[PDB]
Each structure stands twice: as structure tokens, then as C-alpha cells.
Image (tube, coloured by chain):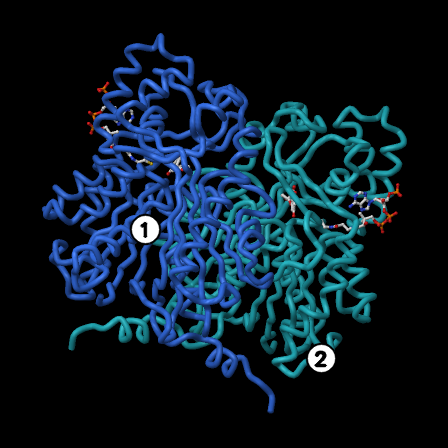
Chain colours: A cyan, B blue
Amino acid sequence: HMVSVEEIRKAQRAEGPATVMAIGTATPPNCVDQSTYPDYYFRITNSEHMTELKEKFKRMCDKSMIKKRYMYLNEEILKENPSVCAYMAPSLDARQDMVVVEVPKLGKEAATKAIKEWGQPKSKITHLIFCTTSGVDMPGADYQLTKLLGLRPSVKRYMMYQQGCFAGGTVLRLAKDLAENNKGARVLVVCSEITAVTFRGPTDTHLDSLVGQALFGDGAAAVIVGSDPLPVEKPLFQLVWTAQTILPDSEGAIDGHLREVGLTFHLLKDVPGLISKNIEKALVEAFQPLGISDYNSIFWIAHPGGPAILDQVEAKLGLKPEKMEATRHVLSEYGNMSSACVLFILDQMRKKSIENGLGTTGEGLDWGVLFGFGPGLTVETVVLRSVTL
Amino acid sequence: HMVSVEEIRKAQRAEGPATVMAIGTATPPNCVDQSTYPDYYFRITNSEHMTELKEKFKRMCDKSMIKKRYMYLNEEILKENPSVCAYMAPSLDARQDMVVVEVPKLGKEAATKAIKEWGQPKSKITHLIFCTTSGVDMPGADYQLTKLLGLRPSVKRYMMYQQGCFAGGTVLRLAKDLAENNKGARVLVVCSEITAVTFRGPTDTHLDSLVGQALFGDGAAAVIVGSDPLPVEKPLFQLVWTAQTILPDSEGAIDGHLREVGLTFHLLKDVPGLISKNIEKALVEAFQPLGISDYNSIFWIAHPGGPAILDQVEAKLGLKPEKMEATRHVLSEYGNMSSACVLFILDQMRKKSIENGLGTTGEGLDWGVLFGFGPGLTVETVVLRSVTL
Ligand SMILES: CC(C)(COP(=O)(O)OP(=O)(O)OC[C@H]1O[C@@H](n2cnc3c(N)ncnc32)[C@H](O)[C@@H]1OP(=O)(O)O)[C@@H](O)C(=O)NCCC(=O)NCCS
Ligand SMILES: CC(C)(COP(=O)(O)OP(=O)(O)OC[C@H]1O[C@@H](n2cnc3c(N)ncnc32)[C@H](O)[C@@H]1OP(=O)(O)O)[C@@H](O)C(=O)NCCC(=O)NCCS
Ligand SMILES: O=C1C[C@@H](c2ccc(O)cc2)Oc2cc(O)cc(O)c21
Ligand SMILES: O=C1C[C@@H](c2ccc(O)cc2)Oc2cc(O)cc(O)c21
């Protein structure tokens, strides 16, 4: 017969739901204690004379519910790059020189761990999604990671630059379509974030910049996503349904500009209220079609943008305190790692489910939700199904 | 009745091949004559003393096979922004201030034209892909376009930043999977490119930067992509098959770095040779499964990185001179508009096929190829099917 586009389409598409088959995570080695961060930060920025501001920063750090963060930046690198320690000094070239190298390097560590868990040859990776908010370059971090891992030159790449904190949801929403539309496709997904682009000295004029310095940390996370798993692959979660929305009345709530001074951060106090005001509508869109209206009966992964977002969502919906445990655990041990955070939380939930002998990767529950929150104000929703242990 | 993930997946997916249903294009109003550009360029950058370098640049402009380009930048803006006219003065903030506004605005013009051709309500747009190599911001150009067009707030966005010249292929590879995997999905795709980020003054120390000043122009293009066309929709092309690859021995052939001086361009003389040496392998991977080995029997869309790429591909494959007509037409009337170019060429091919009464939107042929070329060195391949006129 003559080959038709309709015959090609039927032969090239996959049959089953996109399935998470591996999760790996990595951090820079420099662990920074939150209890002493105000002293460390005001010292390495030569800002000890700003005593009232330091008291404000101490309250921010004490309320952050962060115990520690990992940071590529250390005292030696800051002494070598004093423009990065200024509040607002031309410093983008110094910051780019760091993150164009370190972002794909950290992503390589996470990716190697995901590949090791998957247990399949890396020659079988057909698609790569690389996501960061930390620097840009051409060719991108996707190309650098392809070279570092030795993936096939014909890997289909999606380079997601300057995305922000909702993009852990965005990469899963993308991976889902890549895996489900392509028979055989195995998608490597990497989110890698390094705060060397946003770190800056303190000022009393832009207190929202200081909130960033209290919350943001470094990390990379990788997942393998595919449809129609082989018997030798080990499913962890299914990706069921996705949505992205812009919240009403949220213009300018979270803004970030890449300038000569690096990545600047603008943050309205309305963000927790905006998210908690709109979250039931997002849950109804996702769960009404599944016949689910009890949000204490699903497992939760929420981007921990800060503890006020988690507290206000929990209070608005009446989530029991157990629901945010995995989310709060990652906020505690790592801080806000922008796009990577919800992937660390998915890993933490699988890990705690195994440790406590629960019946599924979703804390013994069947259905789950993953939320990303970021610039827009954008909300990403991913509906998840757990796998039985 | 308990809904299963397998039942959701079956109801959620589209049936047929991703179909281009509209193409719209837009350029800035300032038309720049290539025959006078060396005198304009050397004057406005205060470089008239560099008489030997100006003769070199005249030779580049004369060989470029470009007649004119459209540029957001004009004499008035350049006099207001002397930092942009230096080879390497700090200028990123002035260039960002231009392109963070102008890229989505030019995108809107193109998108409005695509939506008009499509003839459906913009409320039916489910997915938006925005692609640019010109600036970055949070929220991104995708958010700004959603606001400018009044798209639904729940439009699923894919913000493709700092991609480079191959990404007109990339956005079609992405749109194909979004349209095919999602019943009812209608994907708006916008590529918008503004050279305000790369424009800079001449120096004999970086002759590859001067090549960029001869070739790169501004423009935006938009397509609507969907599966399962309604009877009131009008298909133009089907997207059949896609590939991305990195060419062997091509490391550093095309690089671009975002610095305090704007986007810097590095370009090896190796590029045309690398592309022509590797293009047949790309064609065999695409067309041998379709039983096609005569590359004069398919319609051609090639990213016109420069005339030397097109000349060396044509000579390597023994293409008839007519095959590259639509591609050279766009190069002649618009220059190299990075990711947008191949979409202008698809429009030009449809327009010439109508003007000349050919049987199909692909110059009367059934099968076609679209190539993107850019940093990596990356080659994007898209196999197309035309539609009858
Ligand atoms: C920062 C945070 C941990 C502080 O904890 P808290 O429970 O609010 O404690 P407080 O209300 O005492 O706030 C601490 C201080 O930070 C200030 N602050 C909080 N959010 C701020 C913002 N967006 N801009 C400026 N200052 C802010 C408060 O005004 C307060 O100052 P004060 O003690 O001098 O009056 C908490 O407000 C939070 O998690 N906010 C959400 C952060 C967010 O939007 N995340 C998304 C990042 S993309
Ligand atoms: C630029 C171009 C139009 C010049 O036309 P050409 O006649 O084939 O080349 P010529 O040998 O006459 O080149 C003219 C001048 O440009 C110079 N030149 C061409 N490509 C160059 C490069 N990549 N870097 C530096 N100089 C270059 C030549 O050395 C020559 O200088 P000269 O006249 O002082 O000797 C052509 O080389 C071209 O299309 N090149 C491909 C551009 C490319 O790689 N595109 C990708 C963009 S991302
Ligand atoms: O400025 C930043 C920093 C960035 C980031 C966080 C952690 C990290 O490791 C690297 C980068 O996250 C952000 C997220 C935003 O929505 C807006 C922003 O302005 C920023
Ligand atoms: O430096 C640039 C400019 C950019 C561009 C072209 C046209 C336009 O209108 C806007 C930006 O295209 C590029 C494409 C590349 O592969 C590498 C590059 O370095 C560049």
C-alpha cells in the first residue's frame, strides 16, 4: 500500500497514560544553616551597620520554617565577586559565568540518579526537557546536559528558560504529552536552580527582595516519564490531567526582571491570599470530573513558595496537618528551590510511603494533586495517581 | 462507576494528524535597504574612520542576497541610546526595556492575522507556544500575549526563550504533540524576533559579529495548529514527523551569550559545510520510511541562515534551482529573522502556490520538508504534507 499520514499517526502514538518511572535529586555541597543565616548574610554583604534591617531579616528567617538550604555560593566565591554582594551593582556577567556552567552540572547529578533508578540504558531516552530560572545561554543547558550525559545526538530537546516557580508543574504537563503521543518515548525531565543569579545585598527600600534572600535555595531534580511501561520498569505515579491558569486580579503579584544587576525579584504581600482565594476553583476543575470533592482524601504536593502560602491554603480548605507534611519537609530541609521543589516533594512522598510501609507511593491514597505557583500569578495543576507498593 | 486513568486517556486524546490551519506574519515598520546599509551602519555607530572594515561589510552585504530587512531600531532610537551603538558598552537594560515590550507587541500583530485567517473564536485557543531569542522576562512574552489578545486565562502556555534560529522547527515539533494528544486542542504558535538585543557597532577583532549585522532582521509569525479539523476550518499543511539532532564535529559553530553588552553572536565559517555534509543523513531518516529518495519531488522550506547554507545544500543534493525559490524570496525581502523565518517561508509557499494556480499549498507537490538550523549545531526536521487547492 501507499503510506498515509493517518496510518503513520496510528503506528507512532503510545496507548497508556504518562508514567513517572524515576526521580533523582541533587544539591550543591555548601549547607547553610537558617538559624545563623541573618548573621552570615549581613556579614558577607558588609551590611552589619543596618541593625534595624537585620532584625527584620531575622524575623523573616525565623518565620520561614526553613532549617537549612544548599547554595553554590560560598564565602570564597562572594569575596571573589563583590558585585554580587552589592544590593544593585552591575553583576550579570559574573553571575552568568557561574550558572551557565553550574546549572547543567547540578542537573547532570540529578539526571544520573534518575537514570540509575530507571535501570534502562540512557540510549533509550528520546526526549529531554531542561528547565531553569538561573541564567540563559546558546546553545542552552539542554545541549550541555546532552553532552555531559552522553545522550544520543538525536534526543528531542525542550529548553525552558526563565520560567519561575510554577514550572515544576509545566515540565510534567509537557512530559505528559511527549510520552503519550510517541510510542516508545522516554522523557528525561531536569529542573536545575542556582540562586547565584538572584543573591544580592540587603536594602530597606525593597523588603520583598529580602524575602527572596530568606527563602530561595539551590537544587536539581530529574524524572523519567514514559507511557506503556516494560515489565522491568517500575512505575511510581501516573500523570492524569493538567491545567495552567492566571489568577484574576493578580497582575504584578510575582515579577522577575533579568538586568545588568542580575535577576531582580518583586513580590506583593497579596500572594498567599490570591492563591488561597482561587485554590478551590482549581481543585473543582481537576477533581469534579473524577467524582472527588474531599480534598483530605487525596495526597498533596504544593510548591512551598513560602510557609504563608501553605498555611493559608490549609486554613481555607481545612486540610488536616498531615496533608502538607511532605511539602513542609522539603521546605524545611531545602528551602524554595523554584521549579525543582515539587519534584523533591514527589520524591519525599514516595520515600516516606516506603519507610512507613503505606500501601501506595501517595501515602496509601489513590489520587493526588501537584500545584506550582509563580509569576502571572500562574497556577499549574497536575492530577496524579499513585502506584501500589 | 469509578472513572479509571485508562478511560480518561481514551476520552482525552485527539484522532488525526496535527494540521496547520492559519499563518500570519508581521514586521516592524522601518524598512532598511541592504544596498545603503553599510553607509547607514558605519555612520550611526560613529565608525566611518574604519574604511577597510566598511569595505569588508559592503562585501558581506552585497553577497548576503538580502534586498531589505525590517528593524524596530531606527536612527531616532539609536541616537537616544548611544550604549547600543558602541561595540561593547553596557546596554542590556536599554535593550531589555525595548524587547520586553516590542516582542509581544509584534507577536500580537502576527497572531491577530493567524486568528483572522482561522475564522474561529479566540476563546477556542487551548495552548499557546511563544518563541523568541530577543530578551527574557517573568512573567514572559507568553503571559503578555495572553493579556494583549484576551485569550482565556486557562490557556496552556509554553514559553520558549533564548532558542535561536532552529526553533521555528522546534515550535512545530511541540505543537504537533499538543494538538495530537488533546481532543479539541487548538494551538496558537508565535515566533517574534527583534534584533535590538544583538545590534552593535563594528570591530575588526570580531568579524563574525559583523556577519550578524549584515543578515539578521526583525519579524514575527503565528500559526494555528490542531487535529480533527471542523468543516468550517481550512487546513494548509499536515505535520507528519519530526526530528532534532546535533551535528558531529560542530561544537561552538554558532554560540550566543547574554551579557551586560546584550546578546553576543559567535559564528564559524564551518556552518554551511557542516549543514551540507550532514543534510542527506537527515533527509534519509525522514523520507526513506515514506519511500522517498528524490529530494526534487518534495517542497522545501529551509532556514536561510545565510545564502552560503542554501547554495551548498542545493549543490550537495543536486536540487533544481527552483526548489529554494520560496526560501530565497523570504531571505531577499526580510533577511534572517531567526525562529520566525521558516514560518514566513511556509506562508510564501502557500501564497505563490495560490498566485500560480498550483494543485497544492506545497507548489503542487504532496510531501515537503522544513529545516531549522541553529546553535549546537542543531538541525530540526519537520516532514509536511500539503493540502489540495
Ligand atoms: C516571608 C514570610 C515567611 C514571613 O512570615 P510571616 O508569617 O508573614 O511573618 P510576619 O508576618 O511577621 O512577616 C515577617 C516580615 O516580613 C514582611 N514581609 C512579608 N511578605 C513580604 C513581602 N512580600 N514584601 C515585603 N515584606 C514582606 C512582613 O511585613 C514582616 O515585617 P515586620 O516583622 O517588620 O512587620 C511569609 O510572609 C511568607 O511565607 N510569605 C509568602 C512569600 C511568597 O509570596 N512566596 C512566593 C515567592 S515566589
Ligand atoms: C556571509 C556570507 C553571505 C558571505 O558571502 P560569501 O561571498 O560566501 O563569502 P565571501 O568569502 O565573499 O565573504 C565575504 C567576507 O565575509 C567574511 N566572512 C564570511 N563568513 C564569515 C564568518 N563566519 N566569520 C567571519 N568572517 C566571515 C569572509 O571572510 C569575507 O571577508 P573578505 O571579503 O574580507 O575576505 C556567507 O558566507 C554566508 O551566508 N555564510 C553563512 C552565515 C551563517 O553561518 N549563518 C548562520 C547564522 S546563525
Ligand atoms: O529571582 C528569582 C530567583 C529564582 C530562583 C530561585 C531559586 C534558585 O535556586 C534559582 C533561582 O526564583 C524566582 C522565581 C520567581 O517567580 C521570580 C523571581 O524573581 C525568582
Ligand atoms: O545573536 C543572535 C541574534 C538572534 C536574533 C536574530 C534576529 C532577530 O530579529 C532577533 C534576534 O539570532 C541568533 C541566532 C543564533 O542562532 C545565534 C545568535 O547569536 C543569534
Q: Which residue is mark 1?
A: B380
Residue A138 image point, x, y percent: 43, 38
Q: Amino acid at mark 2?
A: Ser
Host chain of mark 2: A
Q: Is residue B135 visible?
A: yes
Disc 2 residue crowd, few under 14, some 14–19, many 20+, Cα 10 Å: some
Q: In the image, is residue A378 above or below residue A353? A: above
Q: Quadrant of residue B189?
A: bottom left
Q: Quadrant of residue B267?
A: top left
Which residue shows up at 77% across the image and 60% down it? A310
Considering only vertical position in the picture, is B122 above or below B351? below
Residue A362 x/y as whole percent: 65, 72
Q: Secondary structure at mark 1?
A: strand
Report whether the residue tagged 1 is closer than 8 Å to ligand 4.
no
- Quadrant containing the C terminus of chain A is bottom right
Q: Residue at x 43, y 59 (%)?
A: B115
- In the rendered image, which quarter contains the N terminus of chain A? bottom left
The image quadrant of residue B287 is: bottom left
Residue A244 seen in the figure: no
Number of marks in picture = 2
Contact (Cβ within 8 Å) of mark 2 with mark 1: no
Q: Are marks 2 and 1 on the same chain?
A: no
Is A336 or A380 nearer to us in this picture?
A: A380
Q: Nearer the viewer, residue A384 or A102?
A: A384
Disc 2 to disc 1, C-alpha distance: 45 Å
Circle 1 Cα neighbour tier, 10 Å, few/some/many (<14 / 14–19 / ≥20):
many
Q: Position of residue A119 (x, y in %)?
A: 46, 63
| Residue in front for this viewpoint, A93 or A344 | A93
Q: Return the residue at label 2.
A: A293
Taking the image as four quarters, which one is ligand 4 found in?
Answer: top left
Say left or right for A354 vs A153: right
